[PDB]
Length: 214
Length: 220
Image (cartoon, rainbow over all chains, first blue to last red; front, side):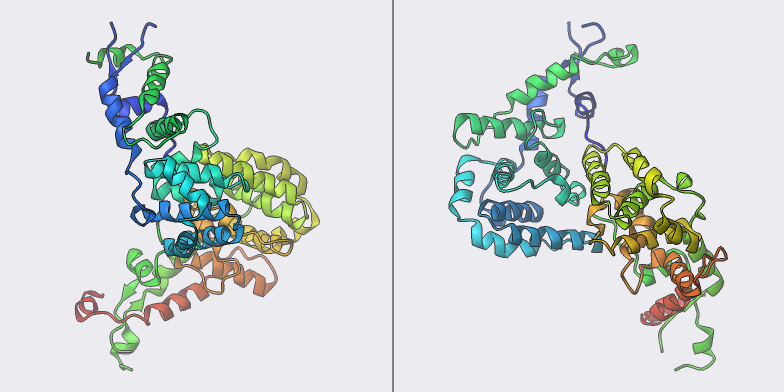
């Protein structure tokens, strides 16, 4: 699917995070439940590119190539991935040579050092790749159906407020940047506060208030 | 993860176009291959042809906007073309269907002399737009890589447009591809469907695939 991104309210309904609250027609949030949801969104620890999903691997390679000023290695990857998205199975393997050549470059090593999760490493690769050129989402539209999470994560790079579906890794990525080090302990509280704020802006119907537990 | 184009054999199974080959049963020659139901295949290919062209206004929003993009490229307005593609790109990220951006360009180029020649010569929305895309590619490259988003919204249009420049179409657009060709070969638009080349090609394709003995027997 290409379903639209969930709003705060939809996300909160989708994961059972709404709770009665003892401001009319308002709900509260299940903090501990929301914490688990946002922790599940962080995804795996980075532990070598080799262990990333193919598409994370390939996109990493593209942004790595951008960081080391190799616009052509990058565009070659994006070109083949486009071509093969039409054919109906992408050839992520085209990324292996660029990876091999830049994974240990100085600039990439600095990024991998600072972030603990696949999603936060690749977010920072993309951010860094953007100091070369523009590298918009639209050059990798094909990602949305492969890795919905990754697509949303990469679409939040440059932005202020993430989609709820990636609020967890967005908040952690920001925390890692603020702390100056990688962090394996999830730092997702910010996603909780934002979910609370958003849910308290939306009025429910009496049916929806009545359907709610404490 | 992505929907892949039907292969010809899967196409033929899906629309139930296979049958026992009467020519190879009353004189064998290759050994384990099905036939095609010519009459059912004409129906199927004719149904892939889609609506008659009858003003851009009556086209699907996606065909409308892509037309406008290719129109602008034929009239060498790269900016107006790219603006549409950007806004369509940007807005597809958000997943809000985004096509009104094209109205200014369509209003501007629709009665241009180059659009008029294309529209004059083709009778179906799919064959107009295929020929707009082909004309648009005499200015620049214009790959299906700016309308990747089209694939999810209009799969038929997506395939038809991915066959402009190809010599062999996907089976799923074989009808309109054949028709587009026949219009180009006749030098005029044709409302009567001209899809016989799609049928020959499918027969040829299907005879390249051996069935197992079980698949042979189930054939009717």
